[PDB]
Amino acid sequence: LLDGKGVEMMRDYANKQLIQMGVKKPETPEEQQWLVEAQQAKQGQQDPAMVQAQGVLLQGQAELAKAQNQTLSLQIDAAKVEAQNQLNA
Amino acid sequence: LLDGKGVEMMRDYANKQLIQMGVKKPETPEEQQWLVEAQQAKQGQQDPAMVQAQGVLLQGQAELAKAQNQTLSLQIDAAKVEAQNQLNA
């Protein structure tokens, strides 16, 4: 679009929008850190469902670890049991 | 828009909305701290789904920590068990 004053603002907004989604190739360094901030915002995005799923996952993994520790502790208590029985016998 | 009295208020509202939305570049210090307040409000938003997801995820991480502590305590109790068995034998 041609340049007045408001349409200049609209064209600048369209400039920033096109640069920020990677569709445009930045030339001027202003566009360069515009893309830099867009990439930073992209890298700092996360959804609640993913976080809840990850929480459930490491809960389950910890309960797996607890089961394995139960195996180990039961085996060691068994070893103590046979040792005590041999000492008594 | 040209200026009367009410349309002056409407144009001032449009000024504030455009500045606070990052589309316009502030010139006057009034617009400067308008943008400052807009940025402060931007830094102070958080959604309930994010906070709930963080709560579940962090519960899971700490229960992972609890599982690891269970590993450590069971191993140490095992060491005590072998020490006691050696002392008895």
Image (tube, coloured by chain):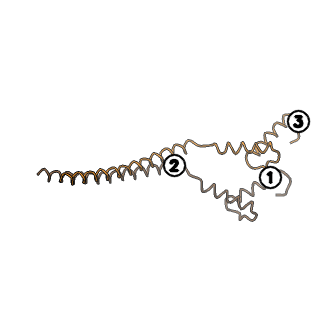
Chain colours: A brown, B orange
Question: Are there few (<14), some (14-19), or many (20+) residues within 10 Å of tag 2?
Answer: few
Find the residue positioned furthest to the top. B5
Q: Chain of mark 1?
A: A
**Cβ–Cβ below 8 Å for labels 2 and 3?**
no
Estimate the x, y position of residue A88 in percent, counting from the top left.
Answer: 13, 50
Q: Chain of mark 3?
A: B
Mark 1 and mark 2 lie on one chain; the one further toward the N terminus is: 1
Judged left or right of residue B16, residue B57 is left
At horizontal 63% and vertical 43% (from top left) the residue drawn is B45
Callout 1 amino acid? Met
Callout 3 amino acid? Gly
Q: Residue at label 2?
A: A49
Q: Chain of mark 2?
A: A
Find the residue positioned furthest to the left. A89
Judged left or right of residue A3, residue A22 is left
Q: Give residue A9's mark.
A: 1
In the rendered image, the vertical position of residue A21 relative to residue B26, given as above or below: below
Q: Give residue B14's mark.
A: none
Q: Where on the picture, by quarter, is residue A79?
A: bottom left
Callout 2 amino acid? Ala
Estimate the x, y position of residue A87 in percent, counting from the top left.
Answer: 14, 52
At horizontal 75% and vertical 56% (from top left) the residue drawn is A14
Judged left or right of residue A12, residue A82 is left
Separation of disc 1 and disc 2 at Cα? 38 Å
Question: Are there few (<14), some (14-19), or many (20+) residues within 10 Å of tag 3?
Answer: few
**Cβ–Cβ below 8 Å for labels 1 and 2?**
no
Of residue A49 and residue B81, the one placed in the foreground of this image is: B81
Q: Residue at label 3?
A: B4
Q: Where on the picture, by quarter, is residue B16?
A: top right
